[PDB]
């Protein structure tokens, strides 16, 4: 089996997996919609009671299976639990990261296209009226991805966006095709430091923004000023948990796959904690101190919150660059922003495609070259669905990137810490660890976490089961139909891999 060269490269590769678009786009939106500081309390708690324990759990499961030559859940779920149904559940460890990858890589190609256009200086040019400043950039984005005037089902991506997507795929391939140590690790040691530098620079530059409408300090205050009136709102807890799952790459089967390349004897405790810690630092300190403070600086808190609620991409691709264009060298500053997003996304995209690649290598015994090329072909082809079908992206991000990750997170925890045995799991986690997991986390993993997630899923299911059936748009049905087809396809591959063994 292939292994990580150094401990540092391992940390940066894992950090690269977690730290991504979720930090600089998803988080700011989530924190702003839930009342800033009010969102921080449930967020930290969710990080302690869910993020950390699951992180360690995924690392352990990854290394455990990796020792036997299996990096994907279909095989690992079977090693921990002997059953056909264990393999079927394991299919999600491929389905989720593949589905997510389909639209994630497209969003990534956006930041690249924007990065390129902002570098060359091809951007809209605003003249004191907020709408007259934002409109040009809204029209810019809509011209790029091909947004319809009314609410029409069809998208019309510009030739450029399409070509940029091809290029993005090519970049993802050139990195993945070189393997774990030569491809991902090498790039991690570069991308990450660069990412951190750009982030710090942007945070500082943004912190210097002060206008008659407010300052960046007002945004930092808003985000870090506690509010206990929102602690009774379940939605805030749900959003915080969802964010923790998405930002830490939990339930994507990505962490497990990456962990399967960790030598059986190497530590996974201190390594995992470091990766997760690096992600939170990059999330709350960096990600939360760029977008939000900037919007609050120019448009004040009320408007900033309004803009955050407006959409997930509205703050990142429209509002922020619009704000920069009003400052000296704002065009180049926008370039740095989109270059930051691109690297963060690139380090993450290669992580959610790896599970698929690792399954082809491990279970179907395909060479690394073929596995990567086929995985790229699949994602690229499937991507057309997100490119040309409106609301398709949201559907995939919901079923896979929201509901699926939590369900899968609960499933993997139940399989590892209950069925496989709590003591055996605990001993497997601490084995070879430079430091040891606090004894208390044994009862967080076994009791607190699964209960919290179970409750969360029940609540979710109750609200979504009626809405699903009554949904007018056909685009969403096509999407559901197709992703379901993907699931069958993967289940069929798992079947073939199972027969080859015999
Ligand atoms: C694409 S890996 C899962 C998502 C990633 N951790 C992010 O926050 O962007
Ligand atoms: Na990343
Ligand atoms: Na993250």
Image: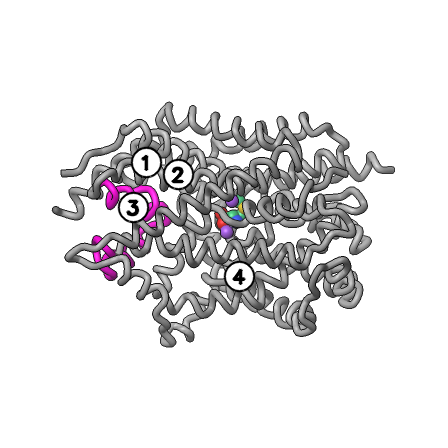
Q: Quickly name the residue at label 2.
A: 390
Q: Quickly name the residue at label 3.
A: 320
Find the distance from the CA under tag 3 to the CA under tag 2: 24 Å
Q: Quickly name the residue at label 1.
A: 147
- Disc 1 crowd rating (10 Å Cα; few below 14, some 14-19, many 20+) is some
At which x and y percent is residue 141?
31, 36
Find the distance from the CA under tag 3 to the CA under tag 1: 19 Å
Q: Residue at x 35, y 51 (%)?
A: 203
Q: Residue at x 27, y 63 (%)?
A: 218
Residues rendered magenta in the picture? 297-325
Closer to the camera: disc 4 or disc 1? Answer: 1
Q: Residue at x 37, y 37 (%)?
A: 153
Tell me if residue 143 is in the magenta stretch. Answer: no
Ligand 1 neighbours mark 2 (CB distance < 8 Å): no
Find the distance from the CA under tag 4 to the CA under tag 3: 35 Å
Whether tag 4 and tag 3 are in contact, CB under 8 A, the answer is no
* Left or right of 292 on screen, residue 492: right
At which x and y percent is residue 122?
27, 28
Q: Quickly name the residue at label 4.
A: 461
- Disc 2 crowd rating (10 Å Cα; few below 14, some 14-19, many 20+) is many
Task: Describe the element under mark 2 as helix, strand or loop.
Answer: loop
Residue 451 falls in image quadrant: bottom right
Task: Describe the element under mark 1 as helix, strand or loop.
Answer: loop
Say whether disc 2 or disc 1 marks the residue closer to the N-terminus.
1
* Dominant secondary structure of the residues highlighted in magenta in the image: helix
> Is residue 20 in view?
yes
Say whether disc 3 or disc 2 marks the residue closer to the N-terminus.
3
């Amino acid at each position: 089996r292939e292994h990580w060269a150094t401990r540092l490269g391992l940390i940066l590769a894992m950090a690269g997996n977690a730290v991504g678009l979720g930090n600089f786009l998803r988080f700011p939106v989530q924190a702003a919609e839930n009342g800033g500081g009010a969102f921080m309390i449930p967020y930290i708690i969710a990080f302690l009671l869910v993020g950390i324990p699951l992180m360690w759990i995924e690392w352990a499961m990854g290394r455990y299976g990796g020792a036997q030559g299996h990096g994907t859940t279909p095989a690992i779920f079977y090693l921990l639990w002997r059953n056909r149904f264990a393999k079927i559940l394991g299919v999600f460890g491929l389905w989720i990261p593949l589905v997510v990858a389909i639209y994630y890589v497209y969003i990534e190609s956006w930041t690249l296209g924007f990065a390129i256009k902002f570098l060359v200086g091809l951007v809209p040019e605003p003249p004191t009226d907020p709408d007259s400043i934002l409109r040009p950039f809204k029209e810019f984005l809509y011209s790029y991805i091909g947004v319809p005037k009314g609410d029409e089902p069809i998208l019309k991506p510009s030739l450029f966006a399409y070509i940029v997507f091809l290029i993005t795929m090519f970049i993802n391939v050139s990195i993945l095709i070189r393997g774990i140590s030569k491809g991902i690790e090498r790039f991690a040691k570069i991308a990450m430091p660069t990412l951190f530098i750009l982030a710090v620079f942007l945070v500082i530059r943004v912190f210097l923004l002060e206008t008659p409408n407010g300052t960046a300090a007002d945004g930092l205050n808003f985000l870090w000023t506690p509010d206990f009136e929102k602690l009774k709102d379940p939605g805030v807890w749900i959003a915080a948990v969802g964010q923790i799952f998405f930002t830490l790459s939990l339930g994507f089967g990505a962490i497990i796959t990456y962990a399967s390349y960790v030598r059986k004897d190497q530590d996974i405790v201190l390594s995992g904690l470091t990766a997760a810690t690096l992600n939170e630092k990059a999330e709350v300190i960096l990600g939360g101190s760029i977008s939000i403070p900037a919007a609050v600086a120019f448009f004040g808190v009320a408007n900033a919150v309004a803009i955050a609620k407006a959409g997930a991409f509205n703050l990142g691709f429209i509002t922020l660059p619009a704000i920069f264009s009003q400052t000296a060298g704002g065009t180049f500053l926008g370039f740095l922003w989109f270059f930051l997003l691109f690297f963060a996304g690139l380090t993450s995209s290669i992580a959610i495609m790896q599970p698929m690649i690792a399954f082809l290598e491990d279970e179907l015994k395909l060479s690394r070259k073929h596995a990567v090329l086929w995985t790229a072909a699949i994602v690229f082809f499937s991507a057309h669905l997100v490119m040309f079908l409106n609301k398709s992206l949201d559907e995939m991000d919901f079923w896979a990137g929201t509901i699926g990750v939590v369900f899968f997170g609960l499933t993997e925890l139940i399989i590892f810490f209950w069925i496989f045995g709590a003591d055996k799991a605990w001993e497997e986690i601490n084995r070879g660890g430079i430091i040891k997991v606090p004894r208390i986390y044994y009862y967080v993993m076994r009791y607190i976490t699964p209960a919290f997630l179970a409750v969360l899923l029940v609540v979710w299911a109750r609200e979504y089961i009626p809405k699903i059936m009554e949904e007018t748009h056909w685009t969403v049905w096509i999407t559901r139909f197709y992703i379901i087809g993907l699931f069958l396809f993967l289940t069929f591959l798992v079947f073939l891999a199972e027969r080859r063994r015999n």
